[PDB]
Amino acid sequence: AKLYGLFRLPRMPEITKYLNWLVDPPVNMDEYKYKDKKREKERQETLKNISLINDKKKLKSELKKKNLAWSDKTLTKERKLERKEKMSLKRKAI
RNA sequence: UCCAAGGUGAACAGCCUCUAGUUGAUAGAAGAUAAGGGAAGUCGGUCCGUAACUUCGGGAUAAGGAUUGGCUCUAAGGGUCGGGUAG
Image (cartoon, rainbow, N blue to C red; front, side, top):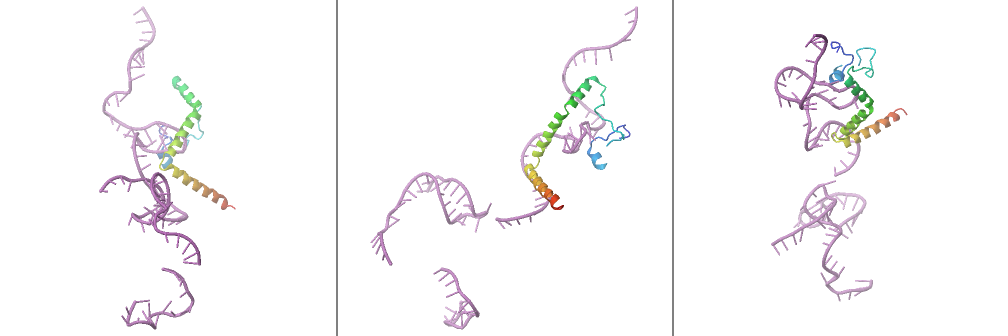
């Protein structure tokens, strides 16, 4: 990454598992200008639509959750585990 | 010789009911258990607590909460248009 001049490790399975900001004072992407007129307005439009695309991805994630292998059973198991763990989280302290 | 509902049984079975048929058969009155001994007899004694898993399609392309951008060569990857200074 230092060879290529990058200042942030791209999100990869390899980076997360086998190994962020290379430049210690981080730089925000909001003030980073594309310098190309046609794509600058597209970037600003996408920035103004951050919450909408985030919610689209959230709904996609929920629908993927409900379509996984025996999802209702998984939610049931999460319910049981959460109840038991949150009961022990106070029963041990008391 | 023909037709042939459902539920439990969760082992053909048995039990109960739906549709449909019966109330026929003179009427009234008034096997089980057992203390102690133990053959002394006789011919002859499916349901409560775990964990991993686990079904169909569509998807190709390394993943699928995150900052997605993802190899080399190899047919096509919607159409079109547009290039300077001087005489």
